[PDB]
Amino acid sequence: DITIGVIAPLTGPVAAFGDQVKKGAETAVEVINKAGGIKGEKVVLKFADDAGEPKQGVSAANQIVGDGIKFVVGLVTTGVAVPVSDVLSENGVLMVTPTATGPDLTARGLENVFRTCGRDGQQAEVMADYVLKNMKDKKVAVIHDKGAYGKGLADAFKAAINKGGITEVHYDSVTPGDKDFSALVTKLKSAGAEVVYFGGYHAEGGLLSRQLHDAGMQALVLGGEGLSNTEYWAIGGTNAQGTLFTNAKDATKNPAAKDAIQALKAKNIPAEAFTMNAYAAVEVIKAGIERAGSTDDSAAVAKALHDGKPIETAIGTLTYSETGDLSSPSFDIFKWDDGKIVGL
Ligand SMILES: CC(C)C[C@H](N)C(=O)O
Image 1: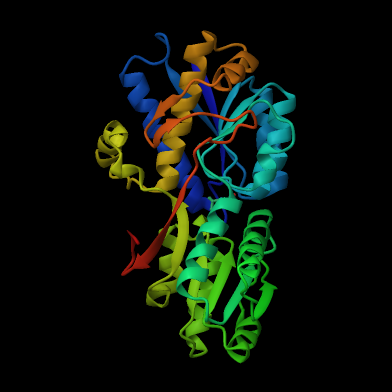
Image 2: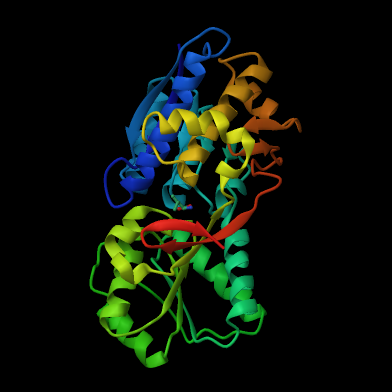
């Protein structure tokens, strides 16, 4: 059997992302096995919970190494991704991230790391352009969650709007697990913040959206794809109406997504971006193995994914750079409307 390890937060404040990655990876595996597996062999998933905690991610990685598993989909959050990557890479375990966007993951010399997603510099620059074009005159604030993702992302947005001439009226952070942001909100009111970019995840983002409105403000919340989960709406309520955030292009618009959509509909799983990217990550591993001709040498599989030939996936046709990033990444802006994600 061909074993694929999945390292993902199944418990804790970001288990909602984990759930998406698991279900995307799961659905891909069923379809491949239904379609005859790899070269005639069953693909199986083995799961290991990082709880969204980098120390526990290392531990999950270690278990993955100790089971002799050679392929991994996961490394979901940037903070976990990088420390997991080292453990995986040292021990000849190939890895594909469907969600981690922190640039450092692919800039430290690693030859067996890949993404089915882009990077923060691009998505912050996308939202910054939108801000400069459409909101040059708004009081803008920049907030993060002190996290590897949160701060990197928010600092990149800040840089891009300062370059375009906009001076933020406030820069600051909150601590994951703290739930009272009334102090920060107090400063936001008094700075007259009309727009607040938040680099972080839903547990914190939702609370910021809520507590802004309770203080009587009508501020527009902006962020990255950490605000793409419906839990952000669950937490934020109607206050999050209008929230804009960046994420990959809607994969459902491509005909390449036909097979994945049907398999998901059949299981009542929504075709969300992370879910699709996790499915495509399994497809990449399969394509790697097919081109290499082996399921035993992960280095050969890695070299094959890096050899310049394009790879067909549910999210589209991919070609990897020497760093393991996508060669043609792109990010669109979406908005939360009445609990649903909509374009434009
Ligand atoms: C699941 C995503 C919100 C994770 C985020 N892109 C990160 O790199 O941490």
